[PDB]
Image: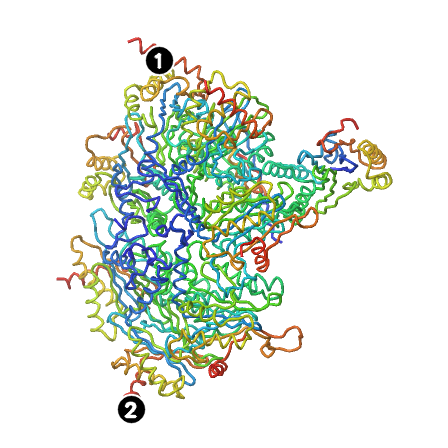
Amino acid sequence: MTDRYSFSLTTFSPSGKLGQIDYALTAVKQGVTSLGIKATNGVVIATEKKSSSPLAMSETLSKVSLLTPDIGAVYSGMGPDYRVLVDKSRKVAHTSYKRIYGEYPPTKLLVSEVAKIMQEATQSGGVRPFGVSLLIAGHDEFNGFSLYQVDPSGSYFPWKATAIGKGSVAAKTFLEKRWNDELELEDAIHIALLTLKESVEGEFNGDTIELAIIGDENPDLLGYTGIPTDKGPRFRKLTSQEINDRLEAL
Amino acid sequence: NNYDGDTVTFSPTGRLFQVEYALEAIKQGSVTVGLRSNTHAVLVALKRNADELSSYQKKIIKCDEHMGLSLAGLAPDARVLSNYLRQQCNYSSLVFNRKLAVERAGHLLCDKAQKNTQSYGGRPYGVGLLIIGYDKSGAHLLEFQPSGNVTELYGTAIGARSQGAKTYLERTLDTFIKIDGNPDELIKAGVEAISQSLRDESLTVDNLSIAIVGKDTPFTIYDGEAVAKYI
Amino acid sequence: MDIILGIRVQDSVILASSKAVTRGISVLKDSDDKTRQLSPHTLMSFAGEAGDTVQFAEYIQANIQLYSIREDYELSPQAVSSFVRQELAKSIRSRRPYQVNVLIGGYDKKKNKPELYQIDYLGTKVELPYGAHGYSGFYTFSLLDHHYRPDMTTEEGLDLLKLCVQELEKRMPMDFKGVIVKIVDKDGIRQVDDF
Amino acid sequence: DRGVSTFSPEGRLFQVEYSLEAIKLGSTAIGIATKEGVVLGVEKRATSPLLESDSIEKIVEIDRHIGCAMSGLTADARSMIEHARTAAVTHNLYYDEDINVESLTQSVCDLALRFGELMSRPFGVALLIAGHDADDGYQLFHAEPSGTFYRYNAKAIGSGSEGAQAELLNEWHSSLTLKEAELLVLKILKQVMEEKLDENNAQLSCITKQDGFKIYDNEKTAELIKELKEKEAAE
Amino acid sequence: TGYDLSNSVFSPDGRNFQVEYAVKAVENGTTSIGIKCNDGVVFAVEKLITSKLLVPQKNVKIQVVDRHIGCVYSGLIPDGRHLVNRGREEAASFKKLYKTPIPIPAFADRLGQYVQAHTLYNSVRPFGVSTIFGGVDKNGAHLYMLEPSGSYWGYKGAATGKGRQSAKAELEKLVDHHPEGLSAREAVKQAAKIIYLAHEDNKEKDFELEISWCSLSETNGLHKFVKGDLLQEAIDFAQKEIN
Amino acid sequence: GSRRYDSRTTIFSPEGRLYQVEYALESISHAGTAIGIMASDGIVLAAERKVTSTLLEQDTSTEKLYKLNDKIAVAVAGLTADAEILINTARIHAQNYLKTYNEDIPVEILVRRLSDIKQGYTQHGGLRPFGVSFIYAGYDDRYGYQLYTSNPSGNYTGWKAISVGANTSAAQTLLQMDYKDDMKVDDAIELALKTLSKTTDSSALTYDRLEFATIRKGANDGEVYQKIFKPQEIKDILVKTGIT
Amino acid sequence: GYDRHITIFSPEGRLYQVEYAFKATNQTNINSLAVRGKDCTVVISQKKVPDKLLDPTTVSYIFCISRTIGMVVNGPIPDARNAALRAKAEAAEFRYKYGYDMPCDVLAKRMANLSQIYTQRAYMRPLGVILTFVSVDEELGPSIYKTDPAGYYVGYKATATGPKQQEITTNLENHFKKSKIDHINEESWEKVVEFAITHMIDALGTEFSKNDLEVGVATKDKFFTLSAENIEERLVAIAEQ
Amino acid sequence: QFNPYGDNGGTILGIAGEDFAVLAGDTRNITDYSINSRYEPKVFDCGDNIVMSANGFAADGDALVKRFKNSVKWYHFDHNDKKLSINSAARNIQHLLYGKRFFPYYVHTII
Amino acid sequence: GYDRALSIFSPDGHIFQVEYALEAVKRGTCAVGVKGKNCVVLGCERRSTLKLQDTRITPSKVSKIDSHVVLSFSGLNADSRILIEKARVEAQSHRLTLEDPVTVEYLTRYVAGVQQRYTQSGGVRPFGVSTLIAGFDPRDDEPKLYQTEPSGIYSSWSAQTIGRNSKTVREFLEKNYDRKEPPATVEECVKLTVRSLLEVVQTGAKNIEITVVKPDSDIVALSSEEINQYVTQIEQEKQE
């Protein structure tokens, strides 16, 4: 034994292509649609909970994940790859930032760290690239609200609104029509639900949709009182009921 | 064929070709004979020269006062394995004040060879060895193959044309096993056995190598004028 | 070793260093040169534990010479002094620290200014008009504090130095066998051969 | 591809057999052992006339009592020479004596099968190791990249070797003087070399008990070449 | 294809062909068996006499682990020795930490996990042996058999090597004809017979029988070789049944 | 074993070329064009973003132009993720040098270090090379204003004007035509945008598809200022130079 | 075609070695099923002892991972025991470090992460097994969490695995569509086991003796397997109604 | 605190003649005021016509002699059964002793 | 660690990775060295596909290893930096331990040793570089010129050339260089060196670089003008 694969498994082909990255992007293309929209006073990220069997309890499978109290993530592609990246992203937010500066990282720098991990799986010995694209929404004091996409290559870009996976080309055109720089968070949620309905075949309700926001501080979710400067997490996952209430107003 | 690129690959019939190829190197080697009585054990080896200007390559290596071997195949591999045996004989003496049993030496060689047959990057040893010794249970002869198989025998031969010597010893078995207390007669039977594997050339004074170990006889090697007596 | 002094005048830096080497009971040598040229316009004098002094100085010299060849360029005295400080600051938390104190006298050809840096074995760096290590400062600084002017000539610097050495030879218990004096200016490094 | 330590179906190591092919492309080297000394000679084979041929170093001292000539990929020999010199000097440090010529040869040969996936390939050079010790007198060994070494009364390696070896088979006898051995090396080198043998494109050396290892001057070799020419013209 | 050129590669039908090729080496070996009796286990193996020059009784094949476990195998003999060396280390480390000698089921998994580990990577080759082993612990007698895949189960009787089919059928008769069980002494006799019967598939050469046993009543729960009179008596009983 | 799956990323072809370096250069030729021009009174860096969307947040976006320190910046052509690995390494080398010598790192010494790192991936380790070419724009008090480029081979060279990425052949010809030694920064700004305007594969050159930067001693008295242009400032210089 | 031998992407973004590991998962030709009661979690699996020389008491694919967690495996036994040993080590280590029993869902996630690594790192092969973890969790109650060679896992109201998983799955779905609750509304685990066996009989269309089944039961603070005689008593009650 | 050294007493004497040499030693072994043995040999025949005694701390002395005898064995293996000369034995023993320069063999050796 | 044997023998006894390294050298710009009676000159070709190049800062082709020794090369530029760094480090290490600067031959033997090591170490490829190393031994006035190549063999030369079209300029040197009378001045030596490059270069413009090395660490690079006067005078004697 020992891992004797100390050479790259991703290499340039004569045409300049990195095959394994292209193929990872193809795996993302097959994935269930997910999207994000940025409002003036918030960000929304959303995806479909495509349950594998009806005996499966799909609330136990979380596609939208808290990374820090003010940062959340969703994906399209290979679920297991996403799950391990979420574990690493949560950890790196602490080890390479919070344990140094005593505060959570700003969205763009946590994105930078995740991106670096994904880049290294594209060059290091004996590994394949991650088969996911991420959408990461967050807030921080000096940059305000933001939304980023990260791809298998490690490249990342900031968006006003975007979509990834299966129905992304159609969803992006739908979003270009409806997006403006004066949207309030409720408007962006409404648009997210409208956009997401197009790519969904079957049931479309609170139990089949997973939706989270980055918005106002939630002092009710802090777990303690008495420190004025601590006002609670900006990340919040909407309930099944909260989604259904907004589906009558649709 | 598609399964002989390395030692870590079984063929579809369950064979290990790199090991079989290592075995083939022994077959190209010069003949060497081993046999024993109840009091002594003898090695005889036909040495090979490169040409008329060259020396005859030594075949017999002493491992301890009570143990040694002869080789056929890759000589540098015999040097590695005999060095290992010297160390193990030595460890047994220093730590336990105990002469290493010939049977235990065989087990250790088997296990050392085996590891080179089951891992990537390695290669099997390309040499065969005949190990003689005298220990607490008397005279012994061992045959080692680089597959790791080690076998205890009254007599045997390895190398090119070893089959002739081996048949001779199979007929003589009942005679040579009884040659107790007469070193010279046991060596004669050894020189006669190895003669059944010669063609074109015969046994000369720089050709022949003999070693003996026994009851009151440290492992000693005879070359040159000391083998004229038996020519 | 024992006394090392430095003074920065108008247009040059002067380093004075004792000649004695003492192995306990005997003065083994009386002509020892306690200095290394790091580059054509930078000189380093040194004192501290036996062996470590010369080992450290030659190590620094080799490194600066390597830099000079790699870049075809002479580092400024400030840059050399920062490199030396870092090496001593790293050394003080080592398994066995270099027990070596240095003065670095250099002429900066870009600014056209002499510069004198004092660095102890801990990596404590300071830029000065004049400096010393060990007990040398205790005997000489009161004289330097009185007579020093920033516009002194080289000859006036040497005369003030003579006075410092005379006070050392009077009040110091150890015989340091005089000093070797070297001048660093725009034309490089030279040794005053009678002092 | 296939392992670097792979056996062929005949029971030979591919890489070792292939390095032997590189050695056949090397310039010729010859050694002759006598009771008065061992001679070592080489073909220099400069690739251009602007190459200063006394910078070609294919005969090399290992110790005062041991010399060495090479043939093949001669850059590969440098670490082998370095090891041999270290081993000779180390043995003298540990034992206050000269190391035996055979023991030195065995030590160099232990390096040879240390390749795998240690160095990445066998050496592409063969060595003639010549010397003297008190126990076995004047000796000449041939060290191969297989890790095998043979002792020889006389031996040739490199591109002209089997033509040279046939010659040595006929000319060697147990009563050769040192002078006779020198002329013999010169004569056989002259035979198998492409260019015309002279003092600038061939080089001689010997090891005697008294004076140790010596590389011959070009002036000294020039005289022996002249002397050879006259004895051949005399029948 | 090319799926069978490298260990640990799944073929499109979910198989590891290198392991299946290891089984071929096992099937090519001499016959070895084990019989679980009332208070113990018996092991026996066929040793082919390749020549007159083999010293009789001298190339012993059955191996002891600790003092209460016997191991026998068919296939590549060196691979079996490597596996037993590891088993001896596992037994020693178990007894060192926990004091008690390693229980047989615990020992079975140690060998199983090690053999299975050699199916996880392409940098190693699977074991070319099937191993029959067991003995007596605090819960009674245990017999196991372990394959190149790492697969093992407990057995009433077991057989491997070239004469495995013949031995199995013989073993099945004993299970049917003795639901109450077999005595250790009966099991030795039966083991001798079954090896003699299985030697038909190997008739070219003569062979030498080798037997061992661990029994609570007969050996005090220690592994011993069957020698001398008791061996001869089992050889005789076997010769009778093939005549 | 594992050898079977090894591409051997660090071998010569029979013509004495490095396969992976050549193929990385092919990758880089599809990246957005980046241009550097050196004047007597400063340096210009101009680069084209790859085909943008209306929903991309431009004012918070960086893909071409990066700050290494206060005196040195780079323009990137190739894999952005690969570039950020090397950029962070270069930022660290610059700080190491500043800590050691108490002087800002000379431009070439930084460039040589990054280029040596790239070289290493072509000779040992069996890993793929970085799919990145850099243009380095910087100032030091030895050579003044300097332009360099490096590529996946780890080779670097100095320039008065240079391009990397897509259409460098066309771009280089245009620069060579209009470049003059006595040219000033405001003239260089115009040349850079005119060249991108002509070589672009887009229909027209607009502010939202550009990144732009200048390094000027237009910082008051003997000191250097880096200016990474905002989207509105790129929009103004497009109008002022008469491209929109 | 070396993208078929190791865990790298094919041109369609697929991992063939993972797909082939799923195929190895059915090599034993065994079906298993798990359901939840009010207070318990039951798992049953077919038992086949095709050789008379085998000791049937040693033939099992149900594992006691910890006091509270049981595991049934669908796949070959060597890989099954590899996973079982690792799961036992992880559960014990978890309790040592964090001072409480490892939850069923957390162990499932951990084993799923390990599996994910084998799909991304080339030198390691996936294990050819599907792992169904069961317990009565102290926070979540009766729990079923299942892991596969892709590194995927999820919780279940009920589940089935093996060659005939679809028949069992649809049978279970039909029952829960009717009852409209996430579990078997039964007090005793004996009756939950009887339900589980009954619906496996219906779905496979085959009858069982006591030696044809393997049963594992999780209750508050322990997981245990039933003997042949406890199973016989189950079978008798099924037949008598 | 553990003291890794001890003192087993003993006295040895080596004299060189014109064509002979002797090495003598008493056979008493002691600790403090007690006798451990009245006959515990302390001068050894090491092969190749060499005799050796390592006097002082007996554990270190036995270890050194044991190592030197082993060195003679390996000198024969490595150098074609060549006889180890007394001058070569002495140099070899220097390297055995200096190898433990910072945790010495607490003995006075004579050959 | 990555261990793969990249340099291995072929059935005909060739090491192809080393031989392909020489092909990289063939492609590199031409380099030439000529020793006079009391000097050595190193001339280098500059490929003129690069205008808009800033020649102040662009890496120069001749490199000082110490104050008395220089190194030039043909082949992969990036590879050459690694050998130049190692050689410079070794030159300072030699001064530090021996208290004498390296001989030209010692420095050559070191660089050549590094090149050989990279032909039989696992996980590395050979240097695609050949070098010319020239200078004067400390306190010696006899000129020195050596050549190394990817295999690690090295030797001394009265005059030598490497890189593209070096077959042609070697042709020229072999007919124009007399050993019994080397270029007796700096002028004669520089003129013979520029002449040799003019066989191959194109414009005698900024295509040709010349560096002169004299005894006692006297090293200087000629400028465009001074070379231009050599180019000029050479062609005016031509039309005859």
> Percent x, y for residue B158?
25, 41
> Percent x, y for residue I35?
51, 23
Q: In the picture, which quadrant includes the C terminus of chain B?
A: top left
Asked if both marks, 1 and 2, belong to the same chain, the answer given is no
Q: Secondary structure at mark 1?
A: helix
**Residue D130 in sight from this viewpoint:** yes
> Percent x, y for residue A203?
39, 80
Q: Specify the amino acid type for callout 1.
A: Leu
Residue F62 vs D208, above or below: the answer is below
Q: Secondary structure at mark 2?
A: loop
D89 displayed left or right of E87: right
Q: Residue furthest right?
A: C146
> Percent x, y for residue F175?
51, 44
F115 displayed left or right of E105: right
A124 displayed left or right of C54: left
Query: Badge 1 local density, few (<14 within 10 Å), some, or many (20+)?
Result: some
Q: Which residue is mark 1?
A: D228
> How far is the residue under mark 1 from the one under mark 2?
119 Å
Total marks drawn? 2
Q: Which mark is residue C161?
A: none
Q: Which residue is mark 2?
A: G241
Of F208 and E42, which appears nearest the observer? Answer: F208
C81 displayed left or right of D122: right
Q: Residue furthest left?
A: E243
Callout 2: chain: G
Query: Residue G78, located in which quarter of the rendered image?
Result: bottom left
Query: Residue G27, located in which quarter of the rendered image?
Result: bottom left
Query: Badge 2 local density, few (<14 within 10 Å), some, or many (20+)?
Result: few
Q: Specify the amino acid type for callout 2.
A: Gln
Of C55 and E157, which appears nearest the observer? Answer: C55
Query: Are the residues flagged by discs 1 and 2 in contact, CB closer than 8 Å?
Result: no
**Residue B218 in sight from this viewpoint:** no
